[PDB]
Structure formats: C-alpha cells, structure tokens
Image (tube, grey):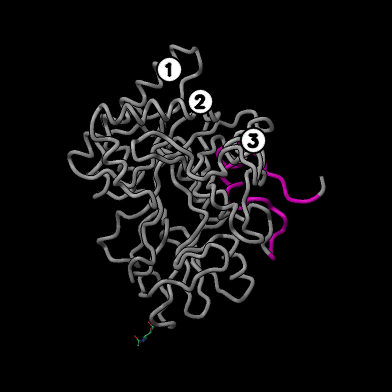
Amino acid sequence: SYIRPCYFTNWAQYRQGRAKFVPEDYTPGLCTHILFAFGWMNADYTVRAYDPADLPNDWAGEGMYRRVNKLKVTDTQLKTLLSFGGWSFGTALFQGMAASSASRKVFIDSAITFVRTWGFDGIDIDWEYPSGATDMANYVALVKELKAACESEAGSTGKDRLLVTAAVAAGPATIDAGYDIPNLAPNFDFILLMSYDFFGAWASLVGFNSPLYATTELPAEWNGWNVDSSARYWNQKGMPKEKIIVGMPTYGRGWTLNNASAINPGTSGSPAKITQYVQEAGVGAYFEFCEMLANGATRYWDSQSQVPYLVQGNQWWSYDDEESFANKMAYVKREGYGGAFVWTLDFDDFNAGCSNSNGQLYPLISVIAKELGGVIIPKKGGH
Ligand SMILES: *[C@@H]1O[C@H](CO)[C@@H](O)[C@H](O)[C@H]1NC(C)=O
C-alpha cells in the first residue's frame, strides 16, 4: 500500500483565528503517518521537547505529544514519528552530534528512549543538510547506527521496531555533497524527498515552488530543478523507488513583481507582501491563496510544469491546488514511487474555512488520501 505521511507542526497552534491548527483538526484516514515537527536536542545531544507545551502541562493540559498520539485511537492504522531538525535548526548541533560513535550513541539511545516514552513509532532525521566528506560519512554512520539500535531494542523488548526515516534534499549539488545513497538506502524505511522550494523569494528569478516538470519559460540551467528530475535522481543513485516518498507542498511562494506587466514564469521580483496568517514574506498558505482568487487574482495554468500560479496586481504566487496534486499523484502511481508526503497539514484548508469553500476538508491533502489511499475525506457539516 502507498505510504502517505503528513507533517504536523507544533507551532501552528499559535496562529490566529482561522489559521490555528491543533491535532484535533486531523480527520481519520487523511494520512498513514504523522511526522511530528519537531523534537529537539540538548547541547549534550540528548533529546528534549521543542515546546514545553508538547509535554503534559498546567497551562494547556495533555500536551501536544499525547494529543497527536491520541489520533491513533480513532485512526487505527495511523503511525506517528518524531522528527528532528528542520531548516531553522541549522546544522551546527547535528555536526557535533554526528562527529563520533560516542556522540551519536548519546543521541541515539536518548531518542529511542524518548520516542518510546512519548508513544511515537519512529524517528525521522531532518538534517538540512549534511555537506562535505566528514558529514557524508558521519551521516551514513548515524543512520546505520540508529537503525541498528532500533533493531536491538526491538529484539530485546519484543516491541515492533521503530521506523527510521529522513527528510532529504532534492537538489543535485546538495544530494551529491551530503548523501552516500547506496550506504543509506538499506538503513531507511523510507525517505521524504523535499521536492519543493525549487524557486522562491530568496532570489529575484520568479518560478515555481514545486514544478512537476521543467518548463522552457525558465532558463535551460534550471531544467533539473523539478519534482520529476529529483525523484529520478534519488532512484538513479541507489534509493529503491518504493522508499522514495514524493514531497507535496500545501504552501506556496510569491514575489512582488519588479514590473507588473511582466507576469510570465521567469520574470523578476522581490519578496511578496507578507500574508495575514503565515507571517513570512514570500510564503503563503493555500487557505490564503483561495482568498486571493476570491478577491480578484487571476489564476494561470503552466502546462509544461503542470502547476498553477496567480497574479494580483504586482503580486505573483506559485502554489499548488487540486489539479497540480492530481497530476502529481498520477506521476507517483505511473512511475511506481512509494507514496507522497505533505508539508504541512496546517497550510491546507484544513477546516474548509475558505470563503469560497464548498465544504471540502483538506481540499489538497484529500487528493492524496483519495488517489493513493482510496480514502474519501468528508465535507464539513452535518452527516
Ligand atoms: C515590463 O514588461 C513588459 C512586458 O514584458 C515590457 O513590454 C516592458 O518593456 C517592461 N517594462 C520595463 C520597464 O522593463
């Protein structure tokens, strides 16, 4: 069966109004796995909660670990994993933790104990990114030794073995500099291919967050910066297709056009104006794009890259929608990859709150649940 993971972020609960996302916004069958972003690390490489509100506490009660893991009562196939790292975490602490067998063992033993204590079924490593010969060998050793310790703990306790996964780079230069893929593949249950953030407001070149295929609207040098090329690259380097889980974004990326009359992919811009709820210039959520379309933005379809974009005055947004998710699910099924994962639950229209919503919960993620899982996610309202 297809693997359909979804990232939960434990800070989305702090967004305002309609954007507040809590574990109780989940709906059964939407995902096969929830990856909890994030678990955290002490200076000595032992594991700690990122947020004090992850743990049982006086000001908010059960804690987000228990509230995510309680989802398994009403979604009996669901598994959960605790993810370590992410972009904001940087690399400094990973580089120190991975430096020796001794320092790796401190983290590994602590993380295994920690996920068993808090009810998670796996450990996900999101180091962004190992780079260079030392990191490359140390990352192989970390994943190898983590899997070995998980097999030992499973054999010793008789419990089902913890999963070992990683969110991994999609860019060829980053892949080649940091990942020895033939010596990682045997030790991962699967990898979460971060096949997004290809273009974004860190540069002036306007392009697509997650194009499925290249387009000749962008310079030839970019023709490998797309979901297809990245998924094939990991397979060619030795990762079995069934372990490649294709990354699906529910956010988008946007520019303020330097020239409001030049609106084609490949134009130029600075970062988009900040959006109300995501509060990060150049980033926006699907439930914000749906309102832009209701407020006069024009939707275009890029037939080469099979993704949409919208234009509102001098604002130009690359995003994903039901149609791009459909092209991409067809691709996953046609090419035989292991499934598709979502970053994030909280950027989809998770509560059908868009002013133009017909009531469908998770309009984007429900495409994955349907097309890879055969699962129909309900509409909001009375049943
Ligand atoms: C703005 O873009 C339009 C269409 O591409 C072009 O005709 C025009 O010359 C551009 N203006 C400037 C100042 O670059």
Q: Is residue 374 magenta?
A: yes
Q: CA distance from mark 1 to mark 3?
A: 25 Å
174 on left or right of 63: left
Membership of 50 in magenta stretch: no
Outermost residue toward the right in this view: 382
| Residue tagged 2 | 116
- Please state the horizontal and vertical placement of residue 87, each as a whole percent of the image: 38, 51
Q: Are marks 1 and 3 in contact (CB under 8 Å)?
A: no
- Label 2 Cα crowd, 10 Å radius (few <14 / some 14-19 / many 20+): few
Tell me the residue that label 3 is attached to.
Answer: 71
Give the left or right position of residue 134, taking residue 97 as reference. Answer: left
Q: Is residue 186 visible?
A: no
Nearest the eye: 215 or 116: 116
Identify the magenta region.
355-381
- Mark 1 highlights which residue? 153
Q: Secondary structure at mark 3?
A: helix
Look at 59% across and 58% down and name the residue there: 15
